[PDB]
Figure 1 (cartoon, rainbow over the protein chains, first blue to last red):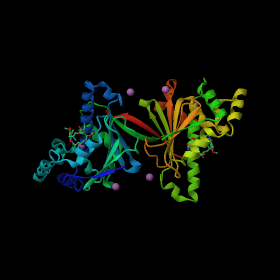
Figure 2: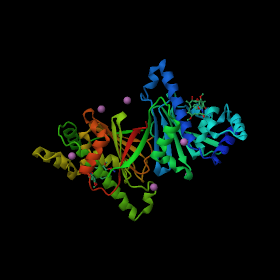
Figure 3: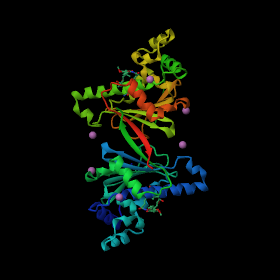
Figure 4: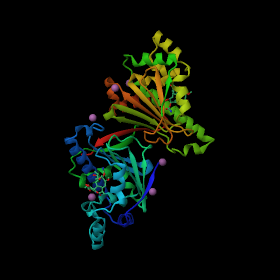
Length: 213
Length: 213
Ligand SMILES: COC1=C2C[C@@H](C)C[C@H](OC)[C@H](O)[C@H](C)/C=C(\C)[C@@H](OC(N)=O)[C@@H](OC)/C=C\C=C(/C)C(=O)NC(=C(c3ccco3)C1=O)C2=O
Ligand SMILES: COC1=C2C[C@@H](C)C[C@H](OC)[C@H](O)[C@H](C)/C=C(\C)[C@@H](OC(N)=O)[C@@H](OC)/C=C\C=C(/C)C(=O)NC(=C(c3ccco3)C1=O)C2=O
Ligand code: NI
Ligand code: NI
Ligand code: NI
Ligand code: NI
Ligand code: NI
Ligand code: NI
């Protein structure tokens, strides 16, 4: 029925630094979320070694990118390990994150945004291209939940009685900024993926809507 | 929380005649559901003439066909008028339907299955290719509901706390028979649509998943 949570202070700062920022190489947000997806797919594949039944909820391991042009939305789905309510809460904003400080200090010094991934806060690069995100997620150990943020000071978390059922995993639902609609285009997606996500152990799927004529 | 309803007797007979049937031209089920979609799109476009706000819930008028190969499922979506709980109940199985009798008598006499559409029971041709259907629907005048049938003697109707939100309209979710998986293939869909659905006033979209390599 949907709870509101406060962002740890530094995490709010990080998000502002990013959402309010010029910078050409915004395309990196795609490497970052594909990198996350991949990590999440590794984790369930590995968990499944001693627990084969964990795969039963969704046998197929993939990454799938669905531009929804109509809604100015882009979605990155993975059939990875997914995240519980508690995980969404703790890992995505309430708890003091590993390198949020360190990363901003590095930016102060002239570091390239590109590095965000190496500080373990790559997730937040999605604010380069988006003013709202929903992380929708289904872990084998909990119900499906939606974490939502507009880069403000808080996020909500809501039991998901609204989205298609993910069997297991996570959909990143990016509400793209108006200047950033190029990331809805098939050719632009293939380009970024080919150039900067060359070594991914899982198939990357791209959902394309074509009018039959 | 999901109610069970009985099929009017003749409607049960019709469904058996169809689901238990040889016959080459099964492809007609596609004409029939595209024909329905179109009718449903006409109806809201027309309703919108004196009530422009009816379009607000989903401004775009389209038909969209999404083969889900993984789940052996094919979906035909329309952004048409959609159907209420009561409508799903009355119009799709509990009430004595216009030409269900007449149509079966016509089949007894040697009529081609193709004609089902002209008896106003084309909907049931989907059992040519499918052993389970979910009709999921969102009318402007009610919540989203799922009507479900395996061709048996009954259907259920359930408040939809499980599927993506249709803004307005209907998704036909066909669980294809194992002999009928050709209707998952892009080329097969374009063929049937081009040959037998040549004159449709609305764009027909086909969702294709392609692996980026
Ligand atoms: C040491 O674990 C890792 C953490 C610490 C926890 C958050 C891990 C999570 O706990 C529940 C969980 O184990 C998930 C698998 C989470 C993943 C990676 C993502 O979700 C999925 N499923 O797509 C992502 O939301 C999309 C979640 C937040 C990640 C943020 C903050 C990051 O920028 N980076 C990050 C990692 C990483 C991997 C590759 C590049 O960076 C990473 O390995 C981490 O922060
Ligand atoms: C005189 O209205 C019509 C009826 C009688 C009522 C059912 C109408 C419905 O009441 C609420 C409603 O007005 C919807 C718009 C329903 C549509 C057409 C479909 O849903 C959508 N939205 O895709 C379909 O489920 C997919 C529903 C059942 C239809 C069956 C039984 C049919 O085989 N045929 C059929 C028509 C038809 C049109 C073209 C070819 O055949 C038709 O015009 C009819 O039965
Ligand atoms: Ni539009
Ligand atoms: Ni916007
Ligand atoms: Ni580049
Ligand atoms: Ni499979
Ligand atoms: Ni089956
Ligand atoms: Ni033909």
